[PDB]
Length: 255
Length: 255
Ligand SMILES: NS(=O)(=O)c1ccc(-c2ncc(Cl)c(Nc3cc(C4CC4)[nH]n3)n2)s1
Ligand SMILES: NS(=O)(=O)c1ccc(-c2ncc(Cl)c(Nc3cc(C4CC4)[nH]n3)n2)s1
Image 1 (cartoon, chains in turn orange, yellow):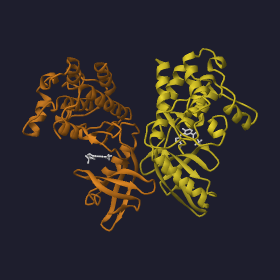
Image 2: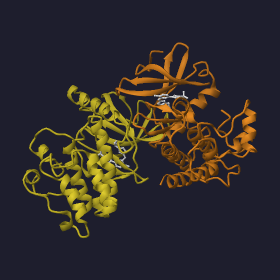
Image 3: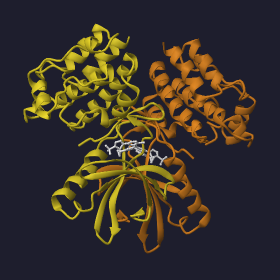
Image 4: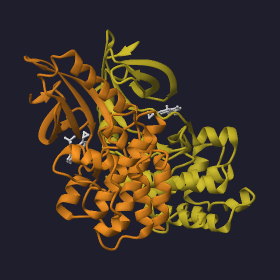
């Protein structure tokens, strides 16, 4: 519809997915640009999907940090088709790391360290509030018009942790590994493992050791190689135990 | 009423003022604690007051920065008395600089620098978005449970700028001076000027030079004295021209 609950004037699609479509809208009451995530409408008439969407809002509303995209409001739209659930979120006028890597190529080491170090902060806060991201990838890290780092989707086979690939339990270390794959990508311009099928990639994550970043892309310090390969360790006990631990090591390479 | 728009379960009063009363509530839809600012109800039945409250929401919603208390939602409550306007805001579980100065005494120089330097950032963002605070005082700067600096009231004679005291035009420099009075207070435990009447204080701000901080409270560097007295300069051209300029000088004393 045109206006959700006669207050949110919907605009251009910023992105879409399997269950929800993300629009850019204007909150008429507050006179501000907001990002509105709406359900597929056909999934809204299902108790399994509705429970997942309403709890996705509640989990995201539970985290208030500058590097995490904020939830402002939630509701339902008066369509003749049925009640339409929506989440009103902080609008981030920016581009994803995926867009940056694809269009501008790899980042300078110092800018890549600055970006991933700020992403570590968002993740460590999440872990402190007992939430594990479960989906860290370039598509979920944006860079603001103010150059600020913003992380979305709190609550793709290339950026899985070995435990995820094996279908085992996950924790903060599973997010650290996933972030290591992102840091590797923004540094070298390529993810740590690639293959013609997703199983070809899943197996590599579990058994095949990672190619050092200095070897894939020229002019990368052996200091950075050691940080990236530590986040990318196969055993979670051998990785950084917190995202704070990872930022601390990155901050050191930078200085 | 009990629940505003059958979604905001009101609780304890955090503070009150001339036009609006600030409560702590729970957004039932999102399962989160929020700060809800409600109008006096008797003022809600007036077009002059309603315009001021609805625009106060819009001005505050226009600023998205970690050191500025966020606006989440706005609305009206279904009371038999009449429509009751309310602003739903970010809950900051903390204490004001006023409470800290009154109960714990002055802050250590290094903690006072850290607090006011972070407040400068909030103000410079406001100025960049064309908003002048107009009311910087200890009561409007809180310290989070996470120790984060949070500024409220975007949109008392002791913390006026000389231009405000003279009833002249105001800008970013009027906020810099006002913040200088706050920095002076958290450092020495006293505001720069005090008198039995508000006019006694207004006159001092305009004509009487400030007593150096090192003289009022022991163990204060002449480096800090120069920063504080620069923010407290009588002519706005002689003060720091931006709040960024002030933070830069504070950051230097600290290091
Ligand atoms: N979620 S998605 O469809 O993969 C997707 C990918 C990229 C997205 C994107 N692109 C450009 C801009 Cl300017 C933007 N602004 C946003 C987006 C959000 C999201 C959290 C609600 N807040 N502010 N978002 S949306
Ligand atoms: N505005 S006032 O009445 O002077 C006033 C003075 C002190 C206040 C206070 N005290 C304790 C806490 Cl734990 C708290 N939390 C808040 C408050 C807000 C305000 C912006 C809506 N967000 N989060 N606020 S309220």
